[PDB]
Image (spheres, rainbow, N blue to C red):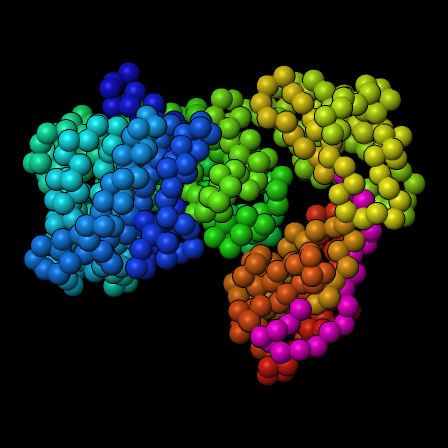
Amino acid sequence: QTDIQSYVADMQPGWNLGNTFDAVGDDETAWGNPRVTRELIKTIADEGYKSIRIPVTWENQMGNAPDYTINEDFFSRVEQVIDWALEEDLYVMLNLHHDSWLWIYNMEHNYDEVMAKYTALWEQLSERFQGHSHKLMFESVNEPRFTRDWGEIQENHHAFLEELNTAFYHIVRESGGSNTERPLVLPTLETATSQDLLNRLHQTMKDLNDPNLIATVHYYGFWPFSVNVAGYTRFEEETQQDIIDTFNRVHNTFTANGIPVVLGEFGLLGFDTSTDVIQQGEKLKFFEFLIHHLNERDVTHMLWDNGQHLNRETYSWYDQEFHNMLKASWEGRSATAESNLIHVRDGEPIRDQDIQLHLHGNELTGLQVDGDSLALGEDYELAGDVLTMKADALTALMTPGELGTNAVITAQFNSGADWHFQLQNVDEPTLENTEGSTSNFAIPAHFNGDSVATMEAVYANGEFAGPQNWTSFKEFGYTFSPVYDKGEIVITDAFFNEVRDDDIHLTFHFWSGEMVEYTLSKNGNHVQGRR
């Protein structure tokens, strides 16, 4: 195992300081995150992360031609954060970030200026960190993209990216000092993973002929699942296969040939809307699967955290279950199940309930409720990987008339994270009539312990309605939003801007399996909603 491979392996796992110095505005606070504190960095290290990516967008901090001197305050701040991370014995990746689509993008029609700014930036960055530890690495440009004439992608784009990567390389290596053997991180185009893009990065790396180079790509999951559209509400076969195919290509092209790979960003795309867009159990299963398959292929990964995962005020995870799954996944596989929900109908006699586990090579060792072990035989049974909750235990754990999460059943295994079943007392969910403007439309709802998975919209003649009309299943959040603490389902302006004046049947799909029909009549800016 070469030095550069040990280096990148020693990075595992990494964390992104998202929507911070990379924010497009007057400074790093411009997108809602606070200024970086020492404790933030310390916490990231304390949570077990061994590397940090510090994306920076520089355009709003640059002076004019020909120097383009970087605002000294901003610069000393990013440097201070880097120094903090190095003191924590972290690896640090520093880049140019949203500069990519802000101006680097327009290289075909503004070549000399783009090259001049790019050059001035990497000169200044090289010079500033010339004496810094090798555990700091440089990444040429984030997710590089260029003006489409006909498509992304086009032949000259590749040449532009190669020119940028090569100019970057020579600037840094020419700086000498610690910059001489400083590891350099180079992206595919758009940091994507199609074979041709992989191959072209490979070629660039061969050309550069340097032992200290790292390939980088990004991954936000199989698109329809990642944003909850077209009916991809569950972590199913296609999403899994997409992970396997993708990182097989990545492994065969780089890792197998001694070029280490950093997955510089991962997450799910819908997180840009909200982490609520992906059902909790399916989200957990996604990340467990992903990290397992990255481990099997020696891919060092770095979580994208724009502020939505670690609470930067409290220095604790918003979603402790999620982070526990990631944490467990760094070491090995965790058992999962078909669902993280157990549904019991409130009106019905309580009976034994089966649940399909996914042991993933592990073994069930116990169940607990509120830190107390449940009774073998009396409360639960296991046959192979099928778990059965006994009727009397469910009766004990539940309250008649109380809809929603009645208890949490914690499944414990010989290895990996605990799996948590939310015990849902549900009733059939109901909707109400309403009427209003396309800019303010909400269906009053009685969720009755249930939760909306997705929503279909078709015209009265069976024609798909709304955005992405190639499917009846509308994108979660963007077109509709369940609001549980307001007891309603919003239908958005964006949805209505792309429907004709007509009757529109909505079909709401719930995770209980319940489906509820609803009808809209849209005329101009008014909409009527009927049960």
Number of numbered labels in the structure image: 0
Rendering coords of residue 40 (x, y %): 41, 38
Q: For residue 138, what is the image quadrant?
A: top left
Q: Is residue 336 visible?
A: yes
Instruction: Name the residue nearer the viewer: 284 or 513.
Output: 284
Instruction: Name the residue nearer the viewer: 527 or 27.
Output: 27
Q: Is residue 413 above or below residue 288?
A: above
- Quadrant occupied by the N terminus: top left
- Quadrant occupied by the C terminus: bottom right
User: Would you say residue 428 sits in the magenta stretch?
Assistant: yes
User: Would you say residue 352 sits in the magenta stretch?
Assistant: no
Q: Is residue 389 above or below residue 449?
A: above
Tell me the residue at 40%/32% (across/down). 42
Find the residue positioned furthest to the bottom.
524
Tell me the residue at 37%/37% (across/down). 38
Tell whether 43 sits left or right of 371.
left
Q: Is residue 302 visible?
A: no
Instruction: Name the residue nearer the viewer: 249 or 346.
Output: 346
Tell me the residue at 19%/31% (across/down). 132
Instruction: Name the residue nearer the viewer: 152 or 510.
Output: 510
Tell whether 324 sits left or right of 400.
left
**Residue extent of the magenta highlight:** 423-442
Rendering coords of residue 215 (x, y %): 28, 34
Tell whether 3 sits left or right of 520.
left
Q: Is residue 164 above or below residue 134?
A: below
Rendering coords of residue 355 (x, y %): 74, 32
